[PDB]
Image (cartoon, rainbow, N blue to C red; front, side, top):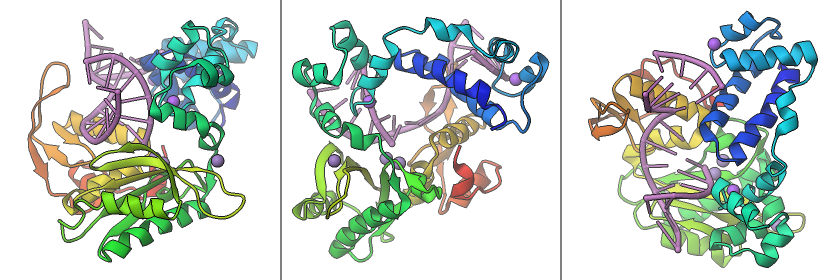
Length: 320
DNA sequence: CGGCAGTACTG
DNA sequence: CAGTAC
DNA sequence: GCCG
Ligand SMILES: [Mn+2]
Ligand SMILES: [Mn+2]
Ligand SMILES: [Mn+2]
Ligand code: NA
Ligand code: NA
């Protein structure tokens, strides 16, 4: 990063807008920040600033104030509420609206939340694991978790295929959670397995709390046996083999990579989701789908890139 | 002016 | 539905 | 916030 002295200050305003609910402005900051993190050289002119995609007038002005002054004065007017809003929205299941409501109602600390707030089932689990869910795990531990889920899955059906996606598959040395994708090449045997799979993972004490228990998605909490172990977030998705390539693409990410590809598909009258790549999609004035189009055959990730006119990228080059 | 990705789950 | 999360 |  040739522009840390700039990016460091912008990230503060980005987080501030984000926890206060100004999501599009925060999105603009996030994009500019990675634009800057990716410039080869330091930014040293206003007109150089505008040269970068994702940096416009208002952002170039801020970068200019920063180098001429070493400071950004907007930093000195950020609401006193922002650190508390960040504290509260780091509870899993509590976002900006819940955080702002708790703040309005007088709560200022997690002790206040614990003793006085009315929590959803999910948020009570989030609070109980507050510290652990802010911690990443070593890659090696993600492997043991993936293998734990796969052994329990293949006990029921040896044909089941399980793959850890997310940051693990992008090759990162540490992982925020473990994202396990499960399918079956027979196109049928994936059905109805969650019941038994999850009950198998509880019987041993591995699965400790459930956050979401859907027909296709499980989100929850696990902990490997023995001393020195933290609770870890675990996500499991079960998909039909027909959708494996698009599900793998989605669940490998990164988030900004997915958003970028899906935005590209839209420009081409196509639609990309965790289910399928579709073409001939009909949309209205506002970019919203009004006609579904046709699913395109995508047996592999490479096919999705190809049909979008893009060169293939291995997972590690998707870490955007 | 207005989109900024597309979807699943919860109550 | 709004809210939240992936 | 940026950009078409
Ligand atoms: Mn993940
Ligand atoms: Mn996850
Ligand atoms: Mn713990
Ligand atoms: Na630009
Ligand atoms: Na949260």
